[PDB]
Length: 275
Length: 10
Length: 100
Image (tube, rainbow over all chains, first blue to last red; front, side, top):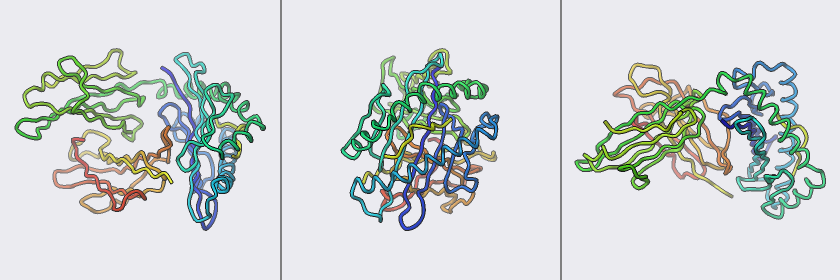
């Protein structure tokens, strides 16, 4: 299937004393493989998947160098943004940056991303063409001019179209045993009776990977969204994911309803019926 | 692998 | 300031069965800012051996975390997640229900 690599960075200012709390994480698809946390003792980029541990000490030194440079950039940012927005030194504020690349089934470049937020609002983002910027307000416009003059888009496009995809292919190869394996959902249905006349049917999908999935109900072969509840997909904690969808039905009419499951790891969609 | 260049202050 | 209240799900890692070492999860998501307090409770009392994922966020910038601890379900013992956030006037408690 298609693949991605994404890096996520959060910095949170700490009024009164010291530098911001900084947390960086790297992902391949839905698998976290690296982390840096300013509050941790090692002060190094750290492995979070077995397959990245194959990398030598020079990988770790270079990643540590870059992640620390990212955190200083964000440190400076928090001060500049405080000034841009006319804010005091009393409040805690947040900067967030995400970047990375998407590749299709052929592992060739599809899309690249680099976007930035301040206090949880859109600030500046690289446009799909990797040549121009979307600045949300006048402060971000000032940043856009700064980044244009310094040719930031050109540097980023080179990374996203080349380096990002090159290393993605590397990680997918090295981590093939997990990263290239799909785990089809394990599915089952539960029944609960709220009253004499009403029942709840819950359709479960467990232990699946990747996270992307579609779960739906049909009544007598037609889509049913009314009287249904769908929970957010959630991590099991062992690298896999869980989801359920539930429908409220008249008691005795259970057999009319079917649950439909679409996932990359299923050659064909799955159908479940209450037995 | 993280980006080197192109990560600039606002 | 944007402030977004967390969604909470409490659930086990594996299907719930008595006497088998399972994992209790509290997944908190959709919140801003990032400072949040999450406790897992056994019979109303705070469990001490609790770990959590590294802070990450969704496309809309909202944060998510997984808190978890080893546990063994029983008929008698009750479990819950207790969450406090700037958007909450009182801590929110969500009970673990093996059927959700």
